[PDB]
Image: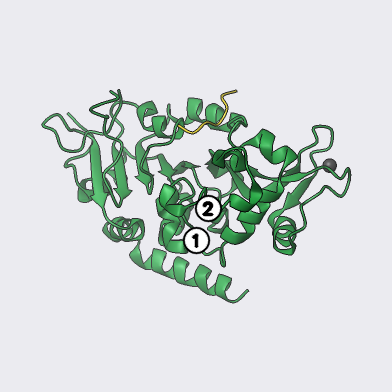
Amino acid sequence: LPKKYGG
Amino acid sequence: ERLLDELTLEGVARYMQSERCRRVICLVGAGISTSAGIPDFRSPSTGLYDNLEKYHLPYPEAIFEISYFKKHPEPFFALAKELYPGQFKPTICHYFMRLLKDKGLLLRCYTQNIDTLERIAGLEQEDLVEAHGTFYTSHCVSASCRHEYPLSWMKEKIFSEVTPKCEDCQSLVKPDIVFFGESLPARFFSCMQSDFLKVDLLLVMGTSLQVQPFASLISKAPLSTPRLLINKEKAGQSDPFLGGGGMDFDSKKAYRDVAWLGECDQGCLALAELLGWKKELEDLVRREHASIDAQ
Ligand SMILES: [Zn+2]
């Protein structure tokens, strides 16, 4: 699943 | 040909009370909790990365990265004590969403906030997609244990400056917020894929729509679905630099997007007033605030 990043 | 008879708050209220508007999705961000005293944790003006010298981090952002936190959790919990709110009193905006629920209009509230105020205001788990998690619950980080702890337990550990450890296995216990480097919640993607087939109105409140993937939710609405932004500043328009599904409030081609610029509480008050809900909202807020003040 997509991970949390700055953007 | 458009669902709103005019691109104003008045047009949105008439649409909400028409037979065409049955299901409302709210998208909310930090702007709905600033009047409750909760700071915007993604704003550089909040200074989250500014006084971390005593923690000797390899870089400022490490304090919110999951792999660093799991080996060095003390900096995060020191910061959490310093930022912990003095009170958890939801705003007029939160209670407006409770009224939406009460009147059978709320399909879902997607929130970027971690402050739990949606739950305190009476939105239930099934009503909520906490896109960045929440402080409402915490879990042991050990995959084989995952013991759950309530916020009262977590708060006591934060304030006593005792790193929270699981009573069953002595692993670290982490608030259920999404740290950088953690997976976003499966529920965010599962609900998005279903909810946006069903939505009649998008109410976007207190978010600058700058953080992904949350911001991209506005592009998931059907093309006909009106979108009302209640926010201090206009947001969600396509970036003349970067740039598909952006807000169009002001062009000759605008047909469904409306911006009400001001404080979120005042915008929700104005909309409730148009709907005939002002007394209901005042009564709910004053009662819930009185109850919280009397704890
Ligand atoms: Zn455990």
Q: CA distance from mark 1 to mark 2?
A: 7 Å
Name the residue: 47% across, 31% down: B195
Whether B1 is drawn above or below B26: the answer is: above
Residue holding disc 2: B118
Whether B142 is drawn above or below A2: the answer is: below
Chain letter of the residue beneath label 2 in the structure image: B
Colour displayed for chain B in the image of the structure: green
Residue B50 showing in the rendered view? yes
Residue B252 position by quadrant: top left
Residue holding disc 1: B90
Q: Which quadrant of the picture is home to ligand 1?
A: top right
Q: Is residue B75 left or right of residue B164?
A: left
Neighbours of disc 2 within 10 Å: few (<14), some (14-19), many (20+): many
Neighbours of disc 1 within 10 Å: few (<14), some (14-19), many (20+): many
Question: Disc 1 vs disc 2: Cβ atoms closer than 8 Å?
Answer: yes
Task: Report the front residue among B78 and B248.
Answer: B78
Name the residue: 20% across, 38% down: B249
Task: Report the front residue among B102 and B166.
Answer: B166
Colour displayed for chain A in the image of the structure: yellow
Question: Could you tell me residue B110's position as x and y percent?
Answer: 48, 40
Mark 2 CB lies closer than 8 A to ligand 1: no
Task: Tell me whether marks 1 and 2 sit on the same chain.
Answer: yes
Name the residue: 68% across, 40% down: B69
Q: Amino acid at mark 1?
A: Pro
Q: Amino acid at mark 2?
A: Glu
Task: Report the front residue among B210 and B254.
Answer: B210
